Length: 121
Ligand SMILES: [Yb+3]
Ligand SMILES: [Yb+3]
Ligand SMILES: [Yb+3]
Ligand SMILES: [Yb+3]
Image (cartoon, rainbow, N blue to C red; front, top):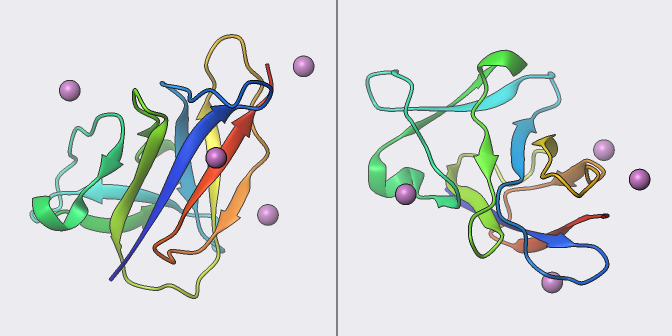
């Protein structure tokens, strides 16, 4: 399996940003949802989510039911536990902190890498 990590930052100052929320979309216009091993919804918090340690499952669902991932105190968020490292996904900023405009969508692959996402004030 594979992971991906993002760091949310202010475009001008490069300071990290807490509280920016994202959904993740695939080519079929479906969005990522985390469940426990019994298929139940799980309450997740800010930051990187260790899917493996917690024995969660990744599923693809409609936008309204998707899991929202949120940058933490150090701007980090993301997860591990992807099956495929060759599929294009897109991080979509659904929850924008006051003071900022949404970042443009970010295409990515689960390639165990980490990249910045920038929000203009
Ligand atoms: Yb907490
Ligand atoms: Yb603006
Ligand atoms: Yb794109
Ligand atoms: Yb950076």
